[PDB]
Image (cartoon, coloured by chain):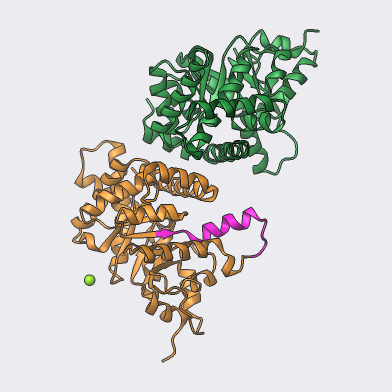
Chain colours: A green, B orange
Amino acid sequence: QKSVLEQLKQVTMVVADTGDFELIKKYKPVDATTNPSLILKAVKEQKYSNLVAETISKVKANNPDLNSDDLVKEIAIEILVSFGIKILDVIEGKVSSEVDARVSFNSATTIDYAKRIIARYESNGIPKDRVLIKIAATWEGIKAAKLLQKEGINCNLTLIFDKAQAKACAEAGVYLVSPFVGRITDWQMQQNNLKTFPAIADDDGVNSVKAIYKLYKSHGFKTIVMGASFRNVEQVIALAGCDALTISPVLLEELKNRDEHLEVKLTQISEADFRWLMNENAMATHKLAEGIRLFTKDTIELENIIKQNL
Amino acid sequence: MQKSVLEQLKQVTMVVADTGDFELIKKYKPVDATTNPSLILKAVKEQKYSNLVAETISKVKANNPDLNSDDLVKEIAIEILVSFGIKILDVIEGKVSSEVDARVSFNSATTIDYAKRIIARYESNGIPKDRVLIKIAATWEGIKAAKLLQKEGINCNLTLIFDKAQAKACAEAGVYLVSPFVGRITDWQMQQNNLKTFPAIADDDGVNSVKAIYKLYKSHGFKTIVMGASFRNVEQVIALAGCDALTISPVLLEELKNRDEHLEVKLTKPQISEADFRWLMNENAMATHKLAEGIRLFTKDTIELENIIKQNL
Ligand SMILES: [Mg+2]
């Protein structure tokens, strides 16, 4: 008779995957995550058009030396931060804000973008303890995160598709990793033209998180495993007990409205090694690249919306 | 006088045979030949070579009695790859391409070491390095290794080329030759659009890829040889007549040898940083998939050959 959402919170850190901060307080998650697709959606849906207009004015005012393209890049960061700030008002934990996906193969520019996000939060009175910087888990992203963590900036290594890939993150001292459960299962279904989801025991996305969790706990890695990007509530339920799960508002609502018993299920690499191991994983090779391309398309669309409102 | 399409092609393009079978090579008279781990495995399994592994083990053990099992297997594998290259060189005037172990494809330093070991093994047999192309997968690390090998006068064949940015980086590194995999690019195109039949030549992504690389090279003054490889049918080869070079399977060479129509000549005459290369490759879903797949398939066959070796130790 307790809801599945309530029971899941007793064994796992529940995180809301959304930039629509007005939806968050219903669910009382500990943390929240945004990404370029979610920010774009929040901006396109217009509930927050005042916040957007006010952000553009402020950045223009404070940056009279920037030409058009530089001004737009700066507003795009300020927007990501303004949504994070509003999220932080309605949660007790941290918000994840993602670096521009276009710098995913450049460690130096990733480091600089990450520090810029942190500085903008600091300028707005938010200390870095409340923020995770999301970075795609290419080799360069991991190398950037290694340095950011040394400087006390916690990172959320996203677009995780392979276990070796997660192990390299942990080896770099990363705060948290996010395996993309639903996209791993999308590949599995696409491979065989499957129209129905696989049994949970045979669901590659669920199994991937299970394997990463078992590796971390047995080796004593402190990096948090946070399953992400789910296709349905059964995939979330399958991972009850995981350190953290970040869940869309639609699935959080399904978990809130479901009253059954929740069974609790869950209780060094060189660059050359990493690239070899990624190469051995056809799904991971494809999905990491695809993830960067899709987040890139959404970041470009957001820039266009900013350009239209200058 | 009138000549077959194969003999006409030799006049405008360097014709190269893509096989480890030296007897077949002999009858098409290509200038160069290319081998790879998949073709070497197929040859090794053929009845003619049933004692080749045991002989090579014998000879290799004898010359290195102090090596551990891993070290030995490795030496036998190079010896086998080189043995097929030598037999091919006995029957052609040009060069043979011999591929480094695909497992070192993300390690420039171990690629360089393997490439020099191949060159040394040929040299031990009296074959100078000007008759050999070392085949390296065109990952960024493969291009870095090739850049350094070329500096030492070791010519490389940069294989598994799927994108014009790889090809441009290879040229910028001064590599001797690049091999775009025409058939495999068309394979992706057909799977992407549920195509039941081959696209028109004008619309064939694999053919167009080589056309684009050839155009880019000539316009930039790059001397790197463009060599189209891995064809699906003879029409794709004919579509590239005039290309610097084309490496063609014996089945397709036989088709060209037997055609007699006129062959119309179709091709006539910023810098890429590592981050730029990785971004451009990332934008190309086909290239990202196909380069990784090519390394995996060559690796699977290299391991299969190692396993044949191990069961004979
Ligand atoms: Mg000679």
Residue A302 x/y as whole percent: 60, 36
> Compared to B200, does B146 lie above or below?
above
Highlighted range, magenta = B179-197
Residue B94 in view (yes/no): yes
Quadrant position of ligand 1: bottom left
**Quarter holding residue B219:** bottom left
Q: Is residue A123 left or right of residue A26?
A: left
Up-down relation of residue A68 to residue B56 (above or below): above
The residue lying at 62 percent from left, 31 percent from top is A204
Residue A113 is situated, as x and y percent measured from the top left of the image, at 45, 28
For the image, the number of numbered tags is 0
Which of A162 and A295 lies nearest the eye of the viewer? A295
Which residue is at a point 58% across and 29% down the rendered structure image?
A: A56
**Image quarter of the C terminus of chain B:** top left
Q: x and y percent of residue A141 in the render? A: 45, 30
Residue B188 sits inside the magenta stretch? yes
> Between B38 and A46, which is closer to the camera in this rendering?
A46
Residue B155, quarter of the rendered image: bottom left
